[PDB]
Amino acid sequence: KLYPAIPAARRRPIRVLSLFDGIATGYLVLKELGIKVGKYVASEVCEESIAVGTVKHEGNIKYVNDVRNITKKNIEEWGPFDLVIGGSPEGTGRLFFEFYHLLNYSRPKEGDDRPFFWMFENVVAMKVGDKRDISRFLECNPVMIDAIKVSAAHRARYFWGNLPGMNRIFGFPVHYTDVSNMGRGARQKLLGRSWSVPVIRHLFAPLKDYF
Amino acid sequence: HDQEFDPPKVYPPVPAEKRKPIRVLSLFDGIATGLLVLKDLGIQVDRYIASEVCEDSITVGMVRHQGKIMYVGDVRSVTQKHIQEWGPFDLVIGGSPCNDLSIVNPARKGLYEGTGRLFFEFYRLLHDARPKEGDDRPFFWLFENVVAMGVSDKRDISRFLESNPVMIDAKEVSAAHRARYFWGNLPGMNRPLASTVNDKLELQECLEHGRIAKFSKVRTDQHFPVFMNEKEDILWCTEMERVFGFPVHYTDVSNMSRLARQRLLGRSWSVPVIRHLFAPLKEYFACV
Ligand SMILES: Nc1ncnc2c1ncn2[C@@H]1O[C@H](CSCC[C@H](N)C(=O)O)[C@@H](O)[C@H]1O
C-alpha cells in the first residue's frame, strides 16, 4: 500500500489521538521530533501515569477523565485527527478494541484524501487465535522490531500502521540507543521498560516529511 | 441508568413508488428466525445472507427456506471485500453467543474471550455494511443479548453500538420467561408490547392434547412443568417451538437428537418479540 506524497511546504500542525497511553509519549516525542504538534489528547483509568502527565507536560493537553467516555461527538469536536497512536502501558483485548473502535471513527471516509497515519503495538504474549483474529480485524500484517540487534535487554514488539519504511530497509539504529540511557536496575524499571524512545521516533520519522 | 447520551437516528419514510425489497445480513443466525419473521410479515426479500458455522442450523435454514439463504461459513472469514461485493445491505441482525457473556457462569471468561469477542466481529461487519456519509438510504441494525450481563459489559456494548438497549421480556407476548436486551435504531424501539391475539400468551395453548400445564409460563424443584396422564413429563420440543413462537414442527430437519434440538431452540430468538421489532419495517420496505 502506497500513497502519493504532499509537498513539504504545507506546514500544518498535527492532530494526535493517543489512546491508553498514560504517560504522555506522543506529545513529548513529537515535541522532540522537530515539528509543531497542534493539540494532544490524554486519558487513562489509572491515576499514577495521569499524575505524571499532569505534572510533567504543564497542562497543554486536553484531558479526558476516562477512556469509557469518548463518543463520536468527542471525535468530531476536537478536529479530525491526522495521527492516531496506541501506546501500550484481561484488559489486553479491552485496550485493543477501544483503540479499534476509536480508530473506526477517526478513519477518513470515502472521498477524503487526507493523509491518515495510525499505529498499534502489542506485547509478545499474544495467543495464536488473538494473532489471526486481530490480523483479520486490522486487515494488515505487523512487523517484528526486536532488541537483540539494537539493545541488551529483551524488547520485542510487532507494529501495525500506515507508516512506511518497515519491510526490508530497516535494520538496527546505532546512535540514539547508545545515547538514550544507562542500564541500572531502577533504570531498568523506569526507562528500560519504557517504550517511548526506541522505535517510536523511527515510526514518526516519515511523518515530518508530510508536515 | 443514564451513563451515555445520544439521540436515535430516525430515517424519513419512503413512499410506495420508490419502494424496494430488503437486503438482509444475518451474522449469528442459528435457527433462521429473522427470515422466518420476515416471510411471516409478508416482506419481499431480495437477498438474505447468513454467516452460520453449525451444520444443524444450516440444515434448519436449507429445509425451512429452500435455498433462499446465501450461506457463509465462519464470521471471521468475512472481510470488507465480501461486504462491498454482496451489495449494500438494508437490515443487519444478530445475537452473539453468550457462553461467556452470561453471568450465570461462576467461572465466566468475559467479553474478550473467543465466544464473546465475536460481537466485535459483528461491529466490524456493522462498520462495513453501514453506508458512508451523504447516503440517505434507510439502514437498520439489530443486536440481541441476554439480560444476565455485568454493568461494565453492557455499558461497553452500549457505547460501542451507540444505542439505548431496550429490555423486552418474552412473557408480555409469549409463554416464556426470558428478558433480552436489544440494541438498534428501529422506529418505535421502546414502544410497548402490542400483544397479538394470534400469539399464544398462555402455556396451555402451546401444549399438545392430554397434557396439563403445571405453571403459567416456562423458564428458559426436581419436577417437570407439565403433567401428562397424572405423571410429570419433560417439556416437548414442538411445544418448545410453540412457546418460542416458531411454527409447529419447525426444528425437525435432520437426524438430530433431543439434546441437539434443545441446544438449537435455547439459543434461538423469540418469534413474537422479533415480529414486534420488525413490524415498522413494513412501511419502509416492500410488501407481499
Ligand atoms: N464464530 C461464529 N460465527 C458464526 N456463527 C457462530 C460462530 N460461533 C458460533 N456460531 C453459531 O452462531 C449461533 C450464535 S448463538 C445465538 C443465536 C441467535 N440468538 C439466534 O437468533 O439463533 C450459535 O448457534 C452458534 O452455533
Image (tube, rainbow, N blue to C red):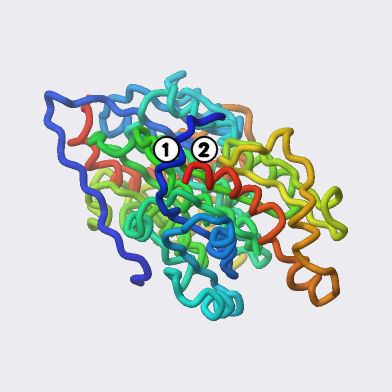
User: Can residue B126 be seen in the rendering of this structure?
Assistant: no
Is the CB atom of the residue marked by disc 2 within 8 angstroms of ligand 1's nearest atom?
A: yes
- Chain for numbered disc 2: B
The residue depicted at 56 percent of the width and 67 percent of the height is A24
Q: Mark 2 belongs to which amino acid?
A: Gly
| Depicted B25 relative to depicted A177: above or below | above
Left or right? Give the position of A135 relative to A50. Answer: right
What residue is disc 1 on?
A: B33
Binning the other alpha carbons within 10 Å of mark 1 as few (below 14), some (14 to 19) or many (20 upward) gives many
The response on whether ligand 1 sits within 8 Å of label 1 is yes
Residue displayed at 37% across by 38% down: A109
Chain letter for mark 1, please.
B
Please report the residue visible at 52 percent of the width from the left and 42 percent of the height from the top: A209
Q: In this rendered view, identify the residue nearer to me: A201 or A185.
A: A201
Q: Position of residue A1 (x, y in %)?
A: 56, 29
Residue holding disc 2: B30
Task: Determine which of the numbered discs, if any, sits on residue A57 in the image.
Answer: none
Image quadrant in which you'd find residue B72: top right
View quadrant of ligand 1: top right
| Position of residue B253 measured from the top left corner of the image (x, y, whole percent) | 54, 28
Query: Is B7 on the left-hand or right-hand side of B88?
Result: left
Which secondary structure lies at badge 2? loop
Pointer 2 with pointer 1, Cβ within 8 A? yes
Whether residue B242 is visible, yes or no, is yes
**Residue B84 position in % (x across, y down):** 43, 26
Amino acid at the residue labelled 1: Thr
